[PDB]
Image (cartoon, rainbow, N blue to C red; front, side):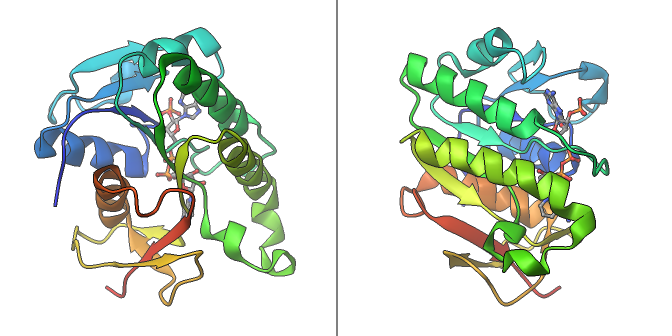
Length: 205
Ligand SMILES: NC(=O)c1ccc[n+]([C@@H]2O[C@H](COP(=O)([O-])OP(=O)(O)OC[C@H]3O[C@@H](n4cnc5c(N)ncnc54)[C@H](OP(=O)(O)O)[C@@H]3O)[C@@H](O)[C@H]2O)c1
């Protein structure tokens, strides 16, 4: 069940690339903000609008949010586990841009670790999780219609469209395919029922 319009942050990442592809195939008119467009597939279905810039730069974010109906956030740091503020700085700029333009809907990916007992989060992942927590707080405090997508391990299994979604939020499987995760990000554009909730998509493959 697919849908049509939007801006994607993090479209060049693992989940971003398939979310972008699914969004264009679905019929969405998609804008992306990318640091470097050579990381978009010079092949795959082409976004309506590519803007080159940095989510840390407010004016770049403002340009990419202008005129959108909703915002999808798949920012991340790849396999870099170092301390970072990119996601929380990005979220702050996204919130400011959404407020200025009257955009209300943001679907943003952090991590299922925000649903764990904090004493059980793997220490090596704590610096990244800290910035996920910072980003989530920014989005919660914004008062915008915010779906918090908190996935467990992101796998590479093909798209099923058959995953489960648990609200607020633990969840019985510890994996979600990147393709199913992107499918779910876009599904969240089709309904208000997850707004203000945390969501944990998962599946057994
Ligand atoms: N198992 C897992 O890996 C797992 C589990 C749970 C949650 N998560 C979280 O899920 C999210 C998505 O992960 P993923 O692996 O699909 O993403 P990823 O491969 O880490 O991609 C990160 C994306 O963010 C973009 N980005 C980074 N810094 C930026 C900046 N300053 N300005 C603009 N764009 C920037 C990257 O662009 P560039 O291409 O220019 O770098 C890329 O598009 C991440 O937050 C991750 O921590 C991951």
